Amino acid sequence: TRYCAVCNDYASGYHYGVWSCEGCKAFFKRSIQGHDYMCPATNQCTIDKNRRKSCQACRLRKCYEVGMMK
Amino acid sequence: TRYCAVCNDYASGYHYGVWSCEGCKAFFKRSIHNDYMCPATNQCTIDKNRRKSCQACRLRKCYEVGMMK
DNA sequence: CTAAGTCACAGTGACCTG
DNA sequence: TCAGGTCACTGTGACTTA
Ligand SMILES: [Zn+2]
Ligand SMILES: [Zn+2]
Ligand SMILES: [Zn+2]
Ligand SMILES: [Zn+2]
Image 1 (spheres, rainbow over the protein chains, first blue to last red):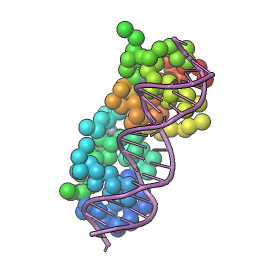
Image 2 (image 1 turned 60 degrees about the vertical axis):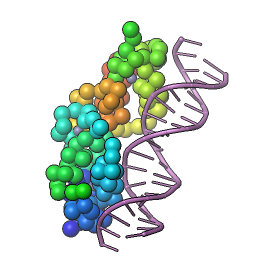
Image 3 (image 1 turned 90 degrees about the vertical axis):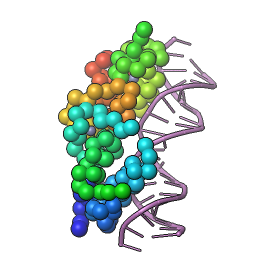
Image 4 (image 1 turned 30 degrees about the vertical axis):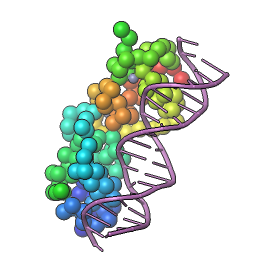
């Protein structure tokens, strides 16, 4: 009930079942809406305030890991 | 056939002293004063489908391959 | 030819509507 | 309150001009 469970940025509220920022909220929104994300490395990127935009594959992976649901 | 020295995509021509696709050419141009951060460990596999994801490793490779500002 | 500009296009997220 | 939209901002790269 404070920080984003996905990128650890200031979370706005409870979105999709986890406390998240508007960024991760919108991201999951679109991801479940319809999109192929490609990880530029080893499917183990560090998702945070300044890396979430870089890897969409690991960001989505994390969205699910932390509990977000459709 | 020529391939982009940075991302292996079909190169458009010889840009900045190296063979590059239009993407890496414009990117390099834009970069030269952007400071980037790799999402992983600075060893990304930069190709057509991932060059947009890591900008740090893209610019790294731009210099590595000999692109001159 | 390449350098350099151009601009439609697509993702992001802060804000808005329901 | 949150889901789902929205749209200005921005980076991209294919194409145009010099
Ligand atoms: Zn977040
Ligand atoms: Zn990744
Ligand atoms: Zn390239
Ligand atoms: Zn990288």
